[PDB]
Length: 315
Length: 278
Ligand SMILES: Nc1nc2c(c(=O)[nH]1)N(C=O)[C@@H](CNc1ccc(C(=O)N[C@@H](CCC(=O)O)C(=O)O)cc1)CN2
Ligand SMILES: O=c1ccn([C@H]2C[C@H](O)[C@@H](COP(=O)(O)O)O2)c(=O)[nH]1
Image (cartoon, rainbow over all chains, first blue to last red; front, side, top):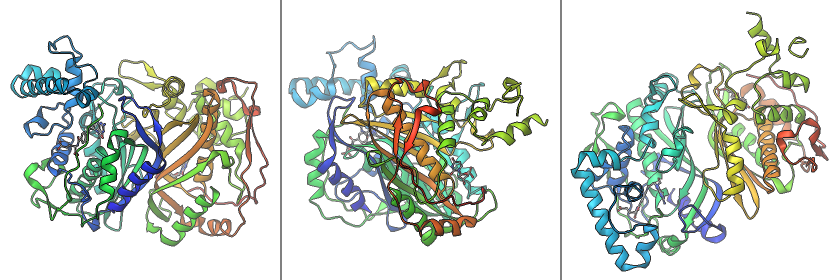
C-alpha cells in the first residue's frame, strides 16, 4: 500500500539521525525496515507525485538485456544514469573543458557554474550518441546490474546467466528455497561506478502465486525508492507472465534508509496529499520470454497522479 | 525481544500456508519477516527453552578465524560435523591425535568470509576489510559480507542459509542486519539469533564501539509439521529476562579470543524441548 512508503518518509523526518555521507550532501537515516505491496491490489507506481513509467521501463529492459553502457538509455531519452558516467569522463585525461570538481553541489549554488555544467553535459550526451569509440570508452559503468544478472564471470573462462537460471528453476522446482539472484560480486565492486544499491533478491511460490523479496543496502527514499519499487514489481509481473503464475507480494527490505537533507521540503509536501488508486499493468500476451519484451509491450493504464515534485540527485 | 520470536512462531501456526519442501516433510511457511533485538536490553539467548551457547561460540570462533578443518571443533566438544567427515573417510582420535588429509571441510562460512577466491587466483578477506572500514569510515553504506557465489552454489549440498549481512554505525553504536533465505523457525532460528548477536558484540569490541541492534530478516520462514507440538509447548511458558554477555576486557583483538573469553551471566532458561532435524 502507498501509505506504507509514506509512513517510512514520515518516520525518517521524525527521528532519523543526521549522518554525513559519501556524496557530501548530508542525510537523515534509519537502519532496518520492511514494507510489503500486494500486487493483486494494483501496480505500485506512487500517486502522491508523478513517477515517469517510461524511464523505469527502459532502465529494467537495459538490465534484462545485460547492458552496462548508457548509450541504450540515451537513445530512449533516459538520463538517470548520466552523472556517474560524466564524472568518469571529467576525471580522465581526455576532458578539456572547465573544471567540474564537485559539480553535483556547485550547480545548486552558482548560476554561472550551472550554465557551464549544462553546456558540458550536452556535449557529453551528443558524443556518446554520435561517436562509437567515445561511447565504448566513456558510456561504460563497469559490471553493474546487467552484467551480474546475465553474465557473472567464472574463474574458468565462462559466465553464469543467473537471472535466466532462476526463471527456469521457478518452472520445475517452485518450492525451492534458493531462488536467488545477487548483484554483489566482491571481485567487481571496486570497478563498478557504484556498488549495487538494490543488492540481492529472492522468489517464493505458493498456491499458484509468485512473490519477490529485495534486500536493498542503501535506499534514497525520496528520489530512488519510488523507482526501485516499481522496477521490482514490473520484474515480478514479467516473470509471472513467462512462468504461467499469478502475482503475490513484493517485500522490500532496507539497510541504510535515508532522506537526503535537500529533499526534506519535497517529502513534507508529498505527505500533505491524499493517496489515489494505483494504476493497472498491461502486458503484451503474445510475448513468451521475459527477454523478448520491448518498450511497446508494457504499459500502465488508469494512472492519475498528483503533480511532479522536483528534487536534485546526490552524485 | 523474545516476544518478537514467539510472535513469529504463533503467526506461522495460525496463518502459515501449507507448502511442500525439498525434504518431503510438511511445513507451514510465510515469506518475508523482520525481527529487531536491542542488544543493550540483554543478550538474546532464548529463556523459554534451553539453547546451548557452547556449540554457538565454538562454531562462531571457527568461522571468524577462517578455519575450515574439524580438528578445532572436536577439541572444543562440538560434534556437529563428526559423522560427515568420517563418511568422507569411509571411501576421530586420529583427527585429534591425518587431520590435514581427512579433516578439511571445503566451501563453508569461514572460507567465504575470509578467503573469497578471485579470477586471477588471489583472495579477498571480506571480514578483515569490513572491520577496517568500520574503524576509518563508519558512515559507509557498503559494510557488506556476502556468502553467496552463483559459481559455487549448484555443486554444494547446502548452499548458505545466511546469504549476506551488513553493518551500520551511529552515535558510537554498531548494528548488524542478516538476510537469511531459509529459516527453520523452531530448531534453527534460536541458534541463528545468538550467533549473529555474538558476532555483533565481537566486532563492536574490536572496533571500540557500543552495541546497537541485531535486525534479522527472513525469506522462507517455516515450521516443520513435526515441530508443531514443541512450538505449542514453548508458547505456554512465561518469558524471563535475557542474560548478560561478558567478554574478556584484557584481550584487545577477538582473533585471539577462545572459549574461555566469552561468557553469559544470569542465564535461567526453562528446560530443553526435543525435536527432529528435517
Ligand atoms: N543518489 C542516488 N544515486 C543513485 C541512485 C539513487 O537512488 N540515489 N540509484 C538507485 O537505484 C541509481 C540511479 N537512479 C536514479 C533514479 C531516479 C533519479 C531522478 O532524478 N528522478 C527524478 C527525475 C526523473 C526524470 O528524469 O524525469 C524524479 O523522479 O523526479 C535519478 C537516479 C544510481 N545512483
Ligand atoms: O543455520 C541453519 C541451518 C539450517 N537451517 C534450515 C532451514 C531449512 O529448513 C534447511 C535448509 O534447507 P534448504 O532451505 O536448502 O531447502 O535448514 C536453518 O534454519 N539454520
